């Protein structure tokens, strides 16, 4: 009698990314057609990225009449676990966040695969004749998410060198060594925090000049505001998926802009988070496939459990309809392929400036095209 | 009085018990009939077998084991599977002994677990010490898709600090037959190669190299596998190609060779068919670490008589009483076992300090040409 | 009317009949049911098997065969043995067909015998044409102790006239396992080698070279054996090492491939155990020459109806009546058989004129890259 | 009641080598002790070197009470055949002549093996730093009898080149090509005839000067008289085994010297043939071993045949006594080894001159020693 779906969110509520609010904004819009079954979305908070803790959560979702599971978006381990269970339950899993170390398979992801992210950074260096590369890896996973990139080019001081940042050790000696090897191109890989920090103690070394060129793999670039660290000659590229083509985009940013200093006014509002963006379109994609599956086969959800070895009969069915999806959300064209990755989407390469951002180029899922 | 240990061993196509589980049933059977360790204490255990690539079941199995009351938990021997048990343990403050490497997230906030397998981060340094030793200018590390190249992070850092042009290449995890891979290598004069894979996958590549004619004195392969010694290098020992690797098993000791000797007088797992190229008669390091995984803990428990196996319950309970402590006794315990001397780090808990034995491929076969260790550097001969 | 032919075939460990004798029993069985040759004439024969390395018996056996009345004598297939029969024949003016090479003294005053096997003196020239073709400066011919290096006299003459530093080396006729031999070769950068031995001995050396790592694109071996095509070069075709040789069997013909096809539908001699490395399914040249040894004579006899098998007696008798002549008809007869076109020299009688097909070892296996002949020189592709 | 032994001789009677006479001279000396059983020797002439013809001969020797078979000495094929039959009859075979392509074994040879002959020529070149070699092979067998030599050194224009002499083609263009390759050392291999002929048309090309050095492998060197072809500076080495140490040597040469122009006075007497020398000592070696075997086991010879598969019981027995023989004949020390070859003998290297020969050096069966 209703279209339910769980959403394991690990985001906070006080000055967070605004994911719990992103889902609500989506459900309201869906229930604005009047005329069928409603659309409900259950929220399942997570505390710490732990397999153990997540397993207990799934045994509370199965008993309910769910159709799909969203997130986590910032919980690598807690994400892989949900996929494994969703696989032995035929309950689709809309992954939208981390991705490491890719047997039972049954799930699709909106977040750009580690293949496209590495291929994008590779196409950018292409227009520069592949200068002296020097990625500033922030962690160990930095090698997996950019696997296709590291293997692509030779590893040396003249082609591509990798330097990892030790914890509680900061980006100090690093940039220094880069200057020694007369390296110009630098590709940092980390969250919005370390991305702002690495460039901070960098600009105070002449590393902010037009002589150097940086490439941020972090998708939280449009929200990453650099005030007092950038110049007019600086070169700091980035990535984005926010498609202004969506008329609801302006209204979306409005909700988060006010809600920010309405609950946690202890800081300013950076900008629409990528996490919330994926969550929004996600809910639509689910209800979209179910809408089509409710046209061919009557859809009935029967309570499952961790103890019972039962599966959702309309599992594999909905999985095919979550493959032929065509939704235009706050992230561009939402389409999937065989494996279940997102394709036929654009990847606008933004570049910071004296005030705001400037789309210097765009990367497609087949060819690059800047300027 | 008696103590109940853990036990989680995945099924195997071989027989009722795998070489892994046998090492455990053999370790907890020697300590009993030996006053050298645990004099007035008898040991028991609860066997809990699970499926391969299955972590969900692995969670309910490990949890059920805590329900019967246990002091520690051994196995499983899989990345994902053991990764789940590790969390359930650190959640209920129950020691989790591990005898195999697994992809551990850098955000690991756990504290109740110990790995006896040589830390790959500290083992990679041993590889680099050989690269610079042979005045290598270039090199091509070829890892298996089974695991990311994070396990070889230290090797990828060399090109930055040290002077070395490293090149990355992936082995077809699908089948051992990868002609095209060895092809491009011979086209790029890639004589220096470093294979990162078990003795199974490694032997599957050597057979290919010989068919590629890449087995000559021009080439020199370095393997990360600690089961190098247990590799039939008969068809190659006459060629001329050099091969180097490591061996943690201290076979240069009577007390060590004595145990392994009695191990071959039990097979159970019939020797694998002569196809892959494995020299039958030598115990695998996978089972060696499991034999030492029981001793390293049997010494930490002997010095802690005040301990009663409580019946915990995952999903909803409180940490084990004598847990936070019994774990500290293990991260400080030392033991001279088969895999040399055991010593866990005083921080991360991982075993980054150990003793390896450099081995090369001479006209006779595989002989030791030196040793290695984190404390000293390299002592060759 | 019918004609009685000869037949001397040594015993074999294989079965009742060897691949040699089968070729004869098969040749004298096709001519009968075929009006193309010997229309109003039926053929018969007297089988006389002897021992290996036994020439004494071979003499009394061949002599007894002449006692039953015969027009010609086939076999045996041994150097010494056939060397004795050859004399008894030329003594009683009775044709002696031979399908195998044998150490013939240069003082050979015989005149009643013909060898279909490609004269090694004229075959050696085919080898030299390849040496100069590959701009070879040096070379090392390695012959088997089974036979002297007189069979390769033409190869030893090259260093005198032509520009080439040839070096001689002998293969241990005792066992196929000759590591030390291949050793010195790799020490002297002897990449250019010419093996002179049958497909049996040759395959026994290739297995060794692969174990010596001497199987790479740096080396290039040339074999004298005409059974090169019938050699399992699977474990080497992927390597890169080049191999060149010859093949007298004209398999590039339907009429030729048709006969061989029906030959594999009879084995009798079970295919040899997979150890030496022989590709089962192809007829050996040894049996090919025997099939053509019957035809080349069946044409010379058809054009000589005036012939009656007389009963001679060795040790004390007079030459055969229609002998001195029937032999001349054979040294002038031509026939298009399996081993290409047959044509005996107009002097020594030996077959010095024939057609060979150059074959090399490419990435797929063994393919023909040209042809050779005494009249023309070399036509490559 | 007597010690018989066959002797398949292929030598002529009219101006031959004097082998049929050599045997007689031996038997007479043996029967000069008076005091045991006599010593008879049957002679079996051969017509042409043929397996066939020789086989018939053996079936006439077996029926007789023979102990050993001597010769042929100039019949390669007719020699190998006799060995084969002697092997299946346990009747020792004293080979003394040809040797090609060495299973049943039971025979000994007095003639220097092809190994020692090649080793001798190798030791000679040793004292010359192995100059430009260029053997003038006369036939195909020239490669087998000197196998150990040809394989010993590299084959080229700077180390060792082999040139064969075609039949009815003579030694003309050959020596010419040698002059082109500035070759100094030349080693000819042929009978006493071609050995005299090759040097004849050679000396008329300045090839007879002291600049060049020749080495004859032919053992008929002491009889090979070169009159009008040699000089005082010429260098023509050779080989010999005639040991003057034997007091009967002078008497031996006397018999052949007169008998030559006593039956065939159509020519002069060259000198003691090597064939006759071997035949003489041969008969002594046989009676010597039998003399020792008649001390341990009573020796009885029973008529055999080609039809019967019987063998001489005292065959293997006599073979061991024909191994431990120590006879000093007209060829030096007569001793055998395991295989049955002759060893511990000397090999005087003679050198022609103005008149006669001159022993320049000597080759032992272990080390060389010239001058």
Image (cartoon, coloured by chain):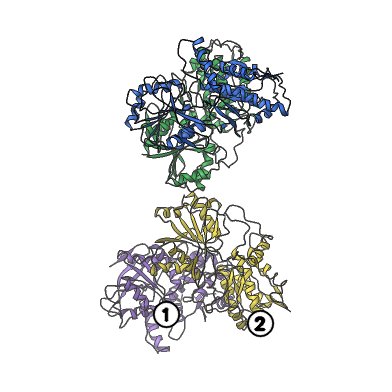
Chain colours: A blue, B green, C yellow, D purple
- Answer with left or right where residue B252 lies relative to residue D358: right
- Report the residue at 70% width, 69% height from top: C29
| Element type at mark 1 | loop
Q: Quadrant of residue B67?
A: top right
| Above or below, A78 relative to D257 | above
**Quarter of the image where one finds residue D189:** bottom left
Do discs 1 and 2 belong to a common subunit? no
In terms of secondary structure, where does tag 2 sit? Answer: loop
Q: Position of residue C87 (x, y in %)?
A: 57, 76
Report which residue position mark 2 lands on: C304
- Whether residue D295 is visible: no
Mark 1, Cα crowd under 10 Å, few <14 / some 14-19 / many 20+, is few
Q: Is residue B225 above or below residue A276?
A: below
Quadrant containing the N terminus of chain D is: bottom right
The mark total stands at 2
Identify which residue, B188 or A261, lies in the foreground.
A261
Q: Position of residue B234 (x, y in %)?
A: 50, 44
Q: What's the CA distance linking mark 1 and mark 2? A: 38 Å
Q: Which residue is identified by label 1?
A: D169
Chain assignment, label 2:
C
Q: Nearer the viewer, residue B228 or D185?
A: B228
């Amino acid at each position: 009698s209703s279209l339910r779906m769980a959403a394991i969110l690990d985001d906070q509520t006080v000055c967070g990314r605004g994911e719990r609010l992103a889902l609500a904004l989506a459900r309201e819009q869906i229930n604005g057609i009047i005329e069928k079954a409603r659309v409900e979305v259950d929220i399942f908070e997570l505390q710490r990225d732990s397999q153990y803790e997540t397993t207990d959560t799934m045994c509370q979702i199965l008993p309910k009449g769910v159709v799909s599971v969203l997130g986590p978006s910032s919980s690598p381990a807690s994400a892989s676990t949900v996929s494994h269970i969703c696989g032995e339950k035929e309950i689709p899993h809309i992954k939208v966040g981390p991705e490491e170390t890719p047997l039972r398979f049954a799930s699709v992801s909106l977040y750009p695969s580690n293949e496209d992210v590495s291929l994008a950074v590779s196409r950018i260096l292409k227009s520069f004749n592949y200068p002296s590369a020097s990625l500033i890896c922030a962690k160990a996973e930095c090698l997996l998410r950019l696997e296709e990139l590291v293997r692509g080019f030779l590893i040396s001081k003249e082609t591509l060198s990798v330097r990892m940042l030790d914890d509680s050790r900061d980006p100090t000696p690093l940039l220094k060594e880069i200057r020694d090897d007369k390296v110009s191109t630098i590709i940092i890989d980390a969250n919005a925090s370390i991305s702002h920090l690495v460039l901070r103690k960098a600009s105070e070394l002449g590393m902010t000049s037009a002589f150097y060129k940086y490439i941020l793999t972090t998708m939280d670039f449009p929200i990453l505001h650099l005030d007092g660290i950038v110049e007019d000659s600086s070169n700091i590229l980035g990535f984005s998926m926010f498609n202004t083509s969506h008329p609801f985009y302006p209204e979306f940013v409005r909700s988060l802009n006010m809600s920010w200093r309405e609950n946690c006014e202890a800081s300013t509002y950076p900008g629409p988070a990528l996490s919330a963006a994926l969550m929004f379109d996600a809910v639509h994609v689910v209800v979209s496939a179910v809408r089509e599956l409710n046209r061919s086969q009557e859809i009935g959800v029967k309570p499952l459990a961790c103890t019972s070895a039962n599966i959702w009969p309309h599992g594999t069915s909905l999985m095919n309809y979550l493959r032929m999806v065509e939704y235009d959300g706050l992230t561009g064209r939402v389409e999937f392929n065989s494996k279940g990755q997102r394709t036929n989407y654009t990847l606008r390469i933004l570049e910071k400036s004296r005030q705001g951002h400037r789309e210097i180029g765009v990367w497609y899922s087949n060819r690059t095209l800047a300027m | 009085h008696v103590l109940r240990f853990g036990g989680i061993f995945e099924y195997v196509e071989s027989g009722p018990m795998g070489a892994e589980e046998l090492a455990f049933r053999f370790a907890v059977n020697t300590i009993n009939r030996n006053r050298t360790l645990l004099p007035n204490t008898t040991l028991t255990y609860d066997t809990q077998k699970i499926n391969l690539y299955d972590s969900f079941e692995a969670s309910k199995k490990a949890c059920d084991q805590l329900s019967l009351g246990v002091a520690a938990i051994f196995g499983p021997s899989h990345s994902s599977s053991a990764n789940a048990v590790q969390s359930i343990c650190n959640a209920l403050g129950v020691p989790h002994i591990q005898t195999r490497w697994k992809h551990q997230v850098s955000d690991n906030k756990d504290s109740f677990y110990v790995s006896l397998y040589p830390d790959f981060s500290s083992l990679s340094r041993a590889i680099l010490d050989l690269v610079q030793f042979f005045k290598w200018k270039t090199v091509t590390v070829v890892y298996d898709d089974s695991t990311g190249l994070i396990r070889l992070q230290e090797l990828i850092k060399a090109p930055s600090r040290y002077n070395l042009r490293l090149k990355i290449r992936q082995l077809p995890a699908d089948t051992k037959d990868a002609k095209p891979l060895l092809k491009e290598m011979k086209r790029g004069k890639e004589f220096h190669v470093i294979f990162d894979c078990s003795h199974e996958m490694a032997a599957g590549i050597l057979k290919q190299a010989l068919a590629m004619g890449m087995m000559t004195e021009y080439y020199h392969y370095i393997f990360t596998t600690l089961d190098l010694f247990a590799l039939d290098v008969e068809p190659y020992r006459y060629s001329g190609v050099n091969m180097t690797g490591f061996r943690i098993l201290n076979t240069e000791n009577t007390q060590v060779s004595s145990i392994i000797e009695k191990w071959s007088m039990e097979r159970l797992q019939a020797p694998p068919k002569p196809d892959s190229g494995l020299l039958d008669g030598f115990m695998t390091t996978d089972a060696a670490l499991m034999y030492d995984a029981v001793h390293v803990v049997s010494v930490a428990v002997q010095q802690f008589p005040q301990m009663t196996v409580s019946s915990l319950q995952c999903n909803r309970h409180k940490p084990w009483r004598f847990g936070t402590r019994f774990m500290s006794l293990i991260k400080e315990a030392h033991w001279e076992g088969l895999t040399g001397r055991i010593t866990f780090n005083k921080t991360n808990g991982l075993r980054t300090d150990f003793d390896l034995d450099v081995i090369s491929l001479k006209e006779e076969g595989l002989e030791k040409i030196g040793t290695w260790d984190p404390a000293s550097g390299l002592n060759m001969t």
